[PDB]
Image (cartoon, rainbow, N blue to C red; front, top):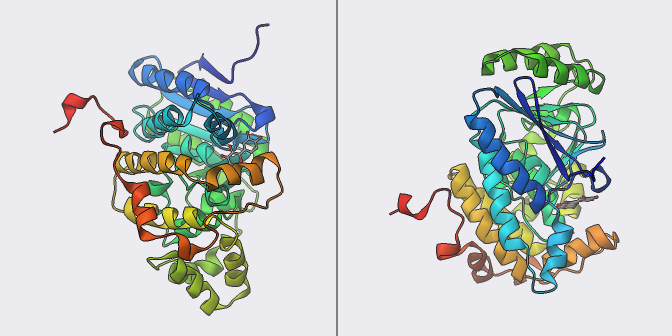
Length: 362
Ligand SMILES: O=c1c(O)c(-c2ccc(O)c(O)c2)oc2cc(O)cc(O)c12
C-alpha cells in the first residue's frame, strides 16, 4: 500500500466520491487537497457517465473542521507564503461547489466548520446527522467567516446568520437542519445505507436524488419533533443584530438584558474587534452580492487580514497553545477605525479574484 492521499477521489457506479482524508487533523483543507478536488469536480461536470458528486469525510468524527489556517499562519512567518494562492484557490472551489453542474451531495456527519462549511453549504444537498457540529468560528481567530459566508449567512432566516457569524455560535445535530445549513437530516445509524443507495442509483436525475434524501429524512427519528434551539431567541436576535455597527449590536444586547443576550454579549466581547467589524460589513455588503462577488470581496479581506496582528495571535491562542487567551490589537472596538476597515475592502486590482479569463471583462 502506498502512502494515503489527503483526499481520495473515486468513481463508484454513477457517482464521483470525494473523501476528505486527514482525520487526525479533522480533515482540515489544504492547498494539495483543493488542487485535487477542483479539477476533478470540473471533469465530473463534463463526464456523461457521472450523475452525482458526493463529498464526505473520513473517520466518523469530522466532515471538515476548516481550511488549514495553522499551516497558512506558519507560512506567513517567512518568505514562502501560502495565503495568496490558498485563499484564491479555496474560494474558486467554493464557487465551483455553488455552481456545480451536476447534483452535489455533502454528507456533513461530524464537525463541519469554516472551510468545511465552504465545501458543503453552497451545494445543492447537505445531509446532517445528530453528530453534525456546525460553526463559523473565525472571529475567535482573527479572521472572518469566509468561504462564501458573506453570501450564505445573510440569506439564512432573519438575522440568524449575523448572529452565527459574529459569535461563532455552535449548532448541533438537527439544529443544523432547522437553521437551513443542512437541507436534510438522517440518523447516523442509517448514513451508510443512504450512501449505498445513492451510489446504487442508475443514471439518476436530480429528482431521483432528492427522492432518496427525502425518504431517509422523513424516517429519521433523532430529535424529529424538537424545536430549533434558537427559535425562542429569534425575535431578540433579529432586533439586536439589525444595527449597522458592532458597538450598536453590543448596546442592543445589553439593553435586551436577558440571560441569553448577556451570555452572547460576553462571547462577542472576547472576539477580535477587527474581525467583528470586518464581519458585520462583509455580511451587510454580501447581502446584496452574488456568490462570485462575495468571494471576490472575501479574497481582499483574506489578504488584508494576513497583514494584521490578530490572525496570527488567534491561531496561537486557539490552535497552537490552546490557551483561549488571545491578546488582540487593537484591543478595543473604538480603535478599529473606519479607515482601517475600508482598507481591508479595497480592490486588489489585477490581483483580485476573478472567475473567468481577463478577455471576458470590460
Ligand atoms: O479554520 C480552523 C481550523 O482549520 C481548525 C482546526 C482545529 C483542529 C484541527 O485538528 C484542524 O485540522 C483544524 O480550528 C479552528 C478553530 C477556530 O476557532 C476557527 C477556525 O477558523 C478554525
